[PDB]
């Protein structure tokens, strides 16, 4: 199609779709979305909608999070293979193993986890609320996955013991070189460096701020600095530049989530033409995964 944007806007209105896009989507998809945000922002937005049809642009665990909290809505995705390789390395078998060895340690699962894994969790957390969630739990020991870096960050801030699963659990996208910060400090002496808690400890410790994408987009609301250096996936640069056109946003390095970039204008148009591919979870998976999500809301309420 020669005008994919205009046909997408035409079909979404005609067929009663709200388009939700994650911060890491390509700019062209962010720009056609009704809302752009982090996984829990989009799931909460979906809960407020009068509309019953959602075109979700992200990866499977996020689309499923929307479906779990919006079970009667039709949720479609343009690429059914779009997934989180980090989430996928944690298994039910590994959770059961660690529960057995540490039975008094609550299982805290990062939202970047499979819906099957969520059915086995005591509580879910986001990168924004993980410290507060783990601080508020009774236990001085927790089981945490699937990101070892976020787990270690949480242990640093809370002073609690955090038992990370799986072994070497990590996001390839956030493995920046610490030397990249050394290089921007010299190139932009007055720039503020913001990096994700999924970054390795040497990167986190050299940044001015550590936070989630949702936290990153609030830092220019209180920090009047002209230049920010951003240590997360490249999609956030577009999001920040749109929100704060008066500031400069510099990627710490080019970091692309290949799965996030599986969604294109062409397969997004195909999704609205065919109203596929529907996100379907067994009723029992929705019911079980909902328990640790409600527990998270209870702790943050
Ligand atoms: O939506 C989310 O919560 C995220 C998702 C992913 S895939 C990476 C980072 C974040 C984050 O917001 O920091
Ligand atoms: S950026 Fe990292 S945590 Fe997020 S979907 Fe991609 S591989 Fe998973
Ligand atoms: Cl619903």
Image: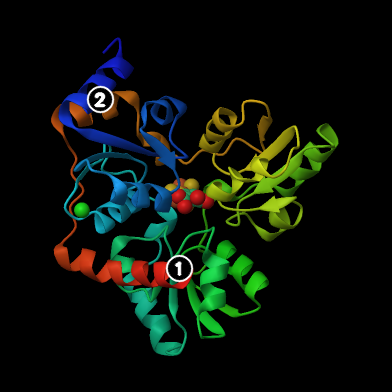
Image coords of residue 43 (percent x, y): 34, 51
Image coords of residue 209 (percent x, y): 70, 51
Pointer 2 residue: 269
Image coords of residue 268 (percent x, y): 28, 29
* Residue farthest top in this picture: 2
Q: Nearer the viewer, mark 2 or mark 1?
A: 1
Please report the residue visible at 54 percent of the width from the left and 46 percent of the height from the top.
173
Q: Can residue 192 be seen in this snapshot? A: yes
Image coords of residue 49 (percent x, y): 27, 44
| Crowd tier of the residue under label 2, counting other residues whose Cα lies within 10 Å: few below 14, some 14–19, many 20 or above | many
Image quadrant assignment for residue 117: bottom left
Q: Is residue 258 left or right of residue 168?
A: left
Q: Does 118 appear above or below 60?
A: below
Q: Earlier in the sequence, mark 2 or mark 1?
A: 2
Secondary structure under badge 1? Answer: loop
Q: Does 165 appear above or below 47?
A: below
Judging depth in this view, the residue of 287 and 262 nearest the camera is 287
Screen quadrant of the C terminus: bottom left
Image quadrant assignment for residue 243: top right
Q: Does 46 appear above or below 295?
A: above
Q: Is residue 142 left or right of residue 42?
A: right
Judging depth in this view, the residue of 279 and 171 nearest the camera is 279
Please report the residue visible at 35 percent of the width from the left and 80 percent of the height from the top.
96
Please report the residue visible at 44 percent of the width from the left and 30 percent of the height from the top.
26
Q: Which mark is residue 301?
A: 1
């Amino acid at each position: 199609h020669h005008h994919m944007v205009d046909e997408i806007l035409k079909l979404k209105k005609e067929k009663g779709y709200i388009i939700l896009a994650h911060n890491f989507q390509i700019p062209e998809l962010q720009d056609i979305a009704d809302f752009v945000g982090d996984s829990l922002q989009l799931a909460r937005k979906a809960m407020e909608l009068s509309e019953k049809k959602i075109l979700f642009l992200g990866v499977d665990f996020m689309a499923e999070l929307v479906k779990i909290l919006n079970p009667d809505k039709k949720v479609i995705v343009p690429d059914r293979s779009a997934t989180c390789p980090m989430a996928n390395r944690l298994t039910p078998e590994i959770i059961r193993e660690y529960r057995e060895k540490f039975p008094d340690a609550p299982v805290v699962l990062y939202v970047n986890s499979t819906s099957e894994c969520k059915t086995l969790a005591d509580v879910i957390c986001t990168s924004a609320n993980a410290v507060e969630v783990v601080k508020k739990l009774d236990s001085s020991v927790v089981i945490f996955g699937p990101d070892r870096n976020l787990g270690e960050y949480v242990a640093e801030k809370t002073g609690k013991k955090v038992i990370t699963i799986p072994e070497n659990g990590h996001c390839p996208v956030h493995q920046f070189n610490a030397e990249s910060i050394d290089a921007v400090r010299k190139k932009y002496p007055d720039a503020k460096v913001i990096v994700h808690p999924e970054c390795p400890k040497p990167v986190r410790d050299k940044a001015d701020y550590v936070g989630s994408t949702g936290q990153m987009e609030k830092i220019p609301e209180r920090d009047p600095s002209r230049i920010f250096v951003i240590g997360t996936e490249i999609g956030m640069i577009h999001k920040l530049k749109k929100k704060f056109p008066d500031r400069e946003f510099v990627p710490l390095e080019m970091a692309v989530c290949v799965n996030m970039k599986k969604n294109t204008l062409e397969n997004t148009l195909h999704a609205l033409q065919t109203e596929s591919f529907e996100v379907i979870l067994p009723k029992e998976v929705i019911e079980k995964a909902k328990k640790p999500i409600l527990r998270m809301f209870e702790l943050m309420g």
